Image: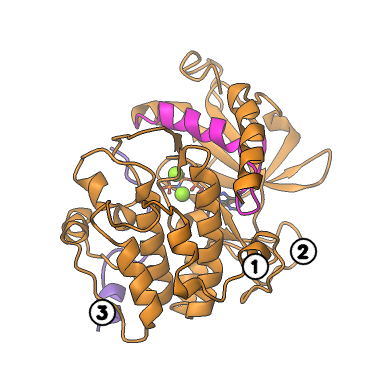
Amino acid sequence: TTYADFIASGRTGRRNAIHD
Amino acid sequence: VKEFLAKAKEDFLKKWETPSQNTAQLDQFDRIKTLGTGSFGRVMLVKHKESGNHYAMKILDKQKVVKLKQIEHTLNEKRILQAVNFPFLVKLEFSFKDNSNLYMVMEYVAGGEMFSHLRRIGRFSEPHARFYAAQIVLTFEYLHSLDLIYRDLKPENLLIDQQGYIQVTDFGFAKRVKGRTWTLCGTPEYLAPEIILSKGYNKAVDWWALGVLIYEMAAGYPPFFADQPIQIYEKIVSGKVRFPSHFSSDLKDLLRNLLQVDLTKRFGNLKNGVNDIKNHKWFATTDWIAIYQRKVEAPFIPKFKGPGDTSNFDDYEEEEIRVSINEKCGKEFTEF
Ligand SMILES: Nc1ncnc2c1ncn2[C@@H]1O[C@H](COP(=O)(O)OP(=O)(O)NP(=O)(O)O)[C@@H](O)[C@H]1O
Ligand SMILES: [Mg+2]
Ligand SMILES: [Mg+2]
């Protein structure tokens, strides 16, 4: 499922803003 | 509405022209616990000695700011935050600086980030998501009318208060601009196509981000996700979106008009402006004046045991705040 693929991804935690 | 906003703009303009400065000092506070971190700063729970009140203090290392080239952005953050006044916007109480850091003392929103509750529960039912969404719609209406663009909408920047209402924080990318701007900034999952494509954009990006927010709240995961940002950007640009079986027809229709890659067709960026969104069927049961007045009964109220309770926030590694004996970047932050 899409949910299962998300939960297994590396971006399920807090997401910081883009800094260069 | 047309009447109200016009009067709030006058208030904003006076403070925008002559900003408040040095309204407190580090020694007036007892530093307690770190509430959160980000790419730029750290936010600490502090207690004001004279009054006994708790606040959330954002600490910015001046040197780190320059290294990351956020000088202009940081100045915008403070200038804009001290000038705004809205029910769903965190309030800036004091601001000051010392040899090494920049400080912004805000009202403490004890309910925690919407992010944590969203992840724990899995997802919000439509009526629950609508409740939060309605507040953001009004917030963007207020912000845009002042020529402001938010640029960093995400559950991590949204706090739940004691009454269960939203408090928008982090104005790190907020900017006052009439016309277009080009900075590539925001959070991967919430970037509008036009930002990634480097073509110059306007307030319409905030409306796209609302689309992503509503989608994430209702589904429990963002519309575009992957392991690396670059992979995400590819998905965002394609524009292909898939909806979960449980999404109602109204919701799907609203999202298709917000997650519209074409600016000439994106809701919020048309002739009727914000009205296209407010008058959409998904919001048919929403009493806009009632939300603004906080008269609506929130679908979720976080547990809160006394002031100073941080049980709704994760734990972070504490770090000593250091203040050099020499002034750092004095000229760069003169107006702060
Ligand atoms: N007024 C507040 N009350 C309680 N917690 C807060 C408040 N303001 C911020 N926080 C918490 O502190 C975190 C970081 O604050 P923030 O202003 O977002 O720093 P940041 O570096 O700009 N984050 P980002 O740019 O998204 O990577 C938030 O995500 C909240 O968890
Ligand atoms: Mg943030
Ligand atoms: Mg930020």
* Residue highlighted by disc 3: A2
| Residue B315 in sight here | no
Report in which chain the residue with disc 1 lies.
B
Q: Could you tell whether B234 is left or right of B303 in the image?
A: left
Q: Nearer the viewer, residue B99 or B239?
A: B239
Q: Colour of chain B?
A: orange
Q: Are marks 2 and 3 in contact (CB under 8 Å)?
A: no
Q: Which circle's residue, 2 or 1, is located before the other in the chain?
A: 1
Residue B31 appears in which quarter of the rendering?
Answer: top right
Name the residue: 30% across, 36% down. B183
What span is colored magenta in the figure?
B68-94
Q: Secondary structure at mark 1?
A: loop
Q: Amino acid at mark 2?
A: Gly
Report in which chain the residue with disc 2 lies.
B
Q: Amino acid at mark 3?
A: Thr
The location of residue B218, given as percent across then percent down, is 42, 75
| Residue B303 in sight here | yes
Q: Secondary structure at mark 3?
A: helix
Q: Nearer the viewer, mark 2 or mark 1?
A: 1
* Residue highlighted by disc 2: B306
Report in which chain the residue with disc 3 lies.
A
Seen in the picture, residue B230 relative to B99 is either above or below; the reply is: below
Q: Secondary structure at mark 2?
A: loop
- Residue extending furthest toward the front: B271
Name the residue: 41% across, 59% down. B210
Q: Is residue B83 magenta?
A: yes
The location of residue B204, given as percent across then percent down, is 36, 49
Q: CA distance from mark 2 to mark 1?
A: 16 Å
Q: Could you tell whether B57 is left or right of B41 in the image?
A: right
Q: Nearer the viewer, mark 2 or mark 3?
A: 3
Chain in purple? A
